[PDB]
Image (spheres, coloured by chain):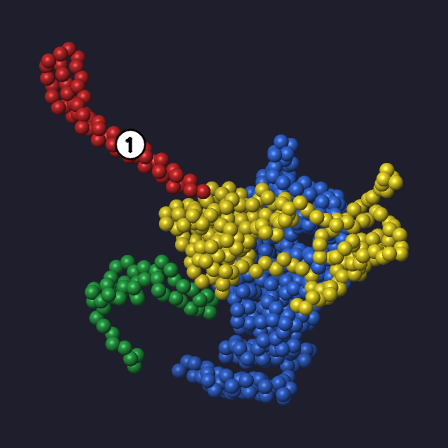
Amino acid sequence: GAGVLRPHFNEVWCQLNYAKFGSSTITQHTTTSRRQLLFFHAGSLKDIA
Amino acid sequence: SFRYTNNLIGALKHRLLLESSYREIASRKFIGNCRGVEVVCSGYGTVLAVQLT
Amino acid sequence: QADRRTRHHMMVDGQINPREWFNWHPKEYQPWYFDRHKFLYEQRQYAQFHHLLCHQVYLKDMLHLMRYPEPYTHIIDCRTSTQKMHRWVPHSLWLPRDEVEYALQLSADEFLDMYGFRKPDKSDDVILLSHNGIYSEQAGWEWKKQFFQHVYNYRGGTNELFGESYSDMNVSDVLSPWKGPFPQSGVFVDKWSKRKVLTRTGPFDRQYEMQDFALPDLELE
Amino acid sequence: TQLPDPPYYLPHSPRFDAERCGTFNKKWLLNLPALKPLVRNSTYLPKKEELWRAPTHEALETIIGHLPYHDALRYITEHSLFLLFPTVLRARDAPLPHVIYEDFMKSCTFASLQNPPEEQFALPSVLLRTLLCMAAYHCTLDADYFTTCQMLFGRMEQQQQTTPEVLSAWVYCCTASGRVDEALTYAKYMADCSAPFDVTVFSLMQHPSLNPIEVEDGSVPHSAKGLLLQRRLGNRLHTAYRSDAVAAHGMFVYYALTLSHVRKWEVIRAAAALGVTLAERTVVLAVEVFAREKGMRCGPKTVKALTHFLAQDGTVGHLLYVLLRARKNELLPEFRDLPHTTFSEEEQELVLQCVAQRARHDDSFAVAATLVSSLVREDDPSELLMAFARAARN
């Protein structure tokens, strides 16, 4: 239904895709404010998982 | 402004001089005599030797 | 646009009647220095509040407090419009300007309940920001109204930190050119003084000075 | 130490605790003897060496504030210091605010520094809002001031700029005088002009004490949490509604807190008759005040207004309770002299069609649409209530 292949989220996978899920690339858009989140940081590799 | 950072530098200079001098006192001999009796101690107050000159 | 004529009844005196009734007298006002280039609260009309102006923290101080923060140097954002804020200044707390005169009237528990962060102590350093530094300046005046000893203002906060080009949108209330002002419609003063206040010498875009008295210069001729 | 409580007939609920701000508290009367050394100390002038070493702004505000009103106006007009206008509002012998507005314009007229007249004779909107809010506090104290306030408005709109701040302050002026219809109609005119209702006027309207000169001065340190709550509630109500619904909520809470319950129900009457779509918070508050008052101070058209606003936006239980209390108060021996609530055919068809529109999507409306239609059509068999109790028990 979602149309995605959901991987294992291994510890090598989290180090590969750390800049997508643990960096400051996240931009939130609400009715209140369209904000660009800076300083967003995943502490360990379990946060990417 | 910057009253905490400028006071933390002055406190750590006080702590660095009190740490570098504690390592000077502890690695030192403190000899006291009364009547030919050499009592040798270290910086920690432990009696190293009770001698006689 | 298109150079609307204004509905004020100011007028230059004619070439026929004598100059009379010198207990009011308009003359041209030219000060010494230009003030339009300056900061808004460093201009001529805000000179009496010159000792009320908060001390300036600069860009390098803001970057040093971004890198190496202090526990009681409170960085506080004073921007009001939530649709115009897009990024977060680090170590900042949101206290919008239009609530500040209420916010400092609360207790510490009520401050924590109504804002989600603890009330700053009166000896703690407070640093305020805005888009241009205008809402932060009024907020610094409200913070200095209460007995807060160390209040600082970063002029041009967000527009120099994040490089934006925004403004606090201060109106600086100027009458619409259909609004006829007070001294034309009113019998508050006699007709000679009403005619002599409403006259001006030159165009009505510059500033003028009103004299309350005048004596004739008998020593010229 | 047991003092009675004024009958606001406001609901005790954690939702409407922001509506409970503005209620006078006897806890402040118990706190009063602790403030006595502070106000005893504040009456004394500072020494000469402290006042001579004082900064310029502090010395100006502390000398002009102690000075007589006309002398302070003379100093302001001589030295063209227009920013000391909020100081002379607080003078010991200052007149009513229309006289102060005329004195402000007179000081701007004869000032030593004459700007261009589009900016010279324009007062700040904070000053005009403070003047009109002082006028509205006086209309709360004495309603027959209102006529002069009308004259005052009749000059200010012709001399200053018609902003939403001064228009919301004039709506508060009309509300405080007991004028229900024109206040709501000015609110609807602001809503059609897409002007936001001012949140400080919305907070001062639901605080029928606290004349705003000492609120901006801050001599009352408590209840600022209530002021912030009312300002945030006004912002929240303006995010989803227009200015007229926010103003009608403020009118309802003001007339509830001034013990003027007849004007409190006239607010709902005029809001239904004019066409103002009430916010859901105001409708729920009106239903709970109706429950607190047991439908005693209510009329037939106010009942019709409440049922229209509940069919438009409201729960089934609130509408059923309002209709059942109206039918029971019709049958009471006290209100037999008063006429009964009767629905004319057009508004009855409108109410039943809106109920059927709600019931096509809602099951709680679909189960009780027949009971609603029986309560509106005035034929109410008790077998429907018995079957309702049987279905509730089973």
| Residue A26 in the image, given as x and y percentages of width and height | 36, 65
For the colour green, the matching chain is A
Amino acid carrying mark 1 in the image: Leu
Q: Colour of chain D?
A: blue
Please state which of residues D286 and D279 is positioned toward the viewer in this rendering: D279
Q: Is residue C207 above or below residue D352?
A: above
Q: Colour of chain C?
A: yellow
- Is the C terminus of chain D in the top left, top right, bottom left or bottom right quadrant? bottom left
Outermost residue on the top side: it is B35
Please give the chain letter of the residue carrying mark 1: B
> Can residue D300 be seen at all in this image of the molecule?
yes
Q: Name the residue located 62 percent from the left edge and 45 percent from the top edge.
A: C47
Please state which of residues C10 and C180 is positioned toward the viewer in this rendering: C10
Label 1 sits on residue: B17
Q: Is residue D287 left or right of residue A35?
A: right
Q: Is residue D143 left or right of residue C34?
A: right
For the colour red, the matching chain is B
Q: Is residue C136 above or below residue D154?
A: above
**The image quarter in which residue D206 lies:** bottom right
Q: Is residue C77 left or right of residue D331?
A: left
| Residue D37 in the image, given as x and y percentages of width and height | 58, 39
Q: Is residue D122 above or below residue C150?
A: below
User: 10 Å neighbourhood of mark 1: few (<14), some, or many (≥20)?
Assistant: few
